[PDB]
Amino acid sequence: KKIETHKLTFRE
Amino acid sequence: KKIETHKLTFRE
Amino acid sequence: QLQASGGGFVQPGGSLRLSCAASGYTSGDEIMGWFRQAPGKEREFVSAISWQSGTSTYYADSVKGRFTISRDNSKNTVYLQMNSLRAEDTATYYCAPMTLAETYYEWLISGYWGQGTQVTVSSAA
Amino acid sequence: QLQASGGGFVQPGGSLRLSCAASGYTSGDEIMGWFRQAPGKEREFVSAISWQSGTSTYYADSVKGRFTISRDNSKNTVYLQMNSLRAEDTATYYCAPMTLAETYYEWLISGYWGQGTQVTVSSAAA
Image (cartoon, rainbow over all chains, first blue to last red; front, side, top):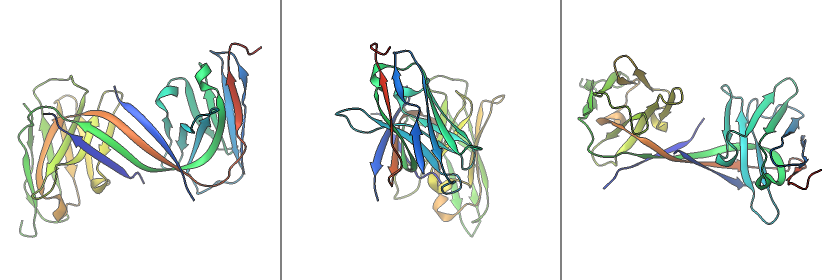
């Protein structure tokens, strides 16, 4: 239905 | 804050 | 059979309402979108509406809070109400069926994260 | 300090309900989310909830329809109800505040459709 990519980006 | 980008792709 | 109409020549701060009238019903409840192109520039997404599992609407950042897309089911017509027009909105506007191919989300997390909890899926449980 | 809890051993097809409880720090974009990490895999987003501009929920494609995120405002607690569990769900799960930095949408068009309609906005209009 909705094709999604969820990227996680941390910090240091 | 939240930015959106909307891209067009024209295809057969 | 799609037909865009309702264009004009207006002062900044004015309004126009674009219409896109469809002849049939497409795929049952697909996505109809607007895009625009100004002279010497590339095509730019403006807005889209789907009325599949309910209504969702999408907008370019530059037109949020000025433009509203809607659909009159009984006339098989999609509307783009353009308020607070600016010189930079000058273009040819087009309506077309669209498909949303992919959506990419970028989520930021900061700092140490907390205590986690273990999930183990096992026929032995 | 944020504590995920409610994990356990579970048979395939079973359920678990995870809890994420804060101490009261509504601030850096009121989004709370869950991510997981399984051996030999990269940390993966699972789900997020914003209760800022109404309730907005987000899910990884592989748990859509199986997992439901919610928030109990009274208790300052976020829940992840995990149904129809499968071996690929085995991981350590973490909750964390998250910010949604950017969304990229990719729209496809096919076919000749119609004339366009010309819009001109200028102070010369009369």
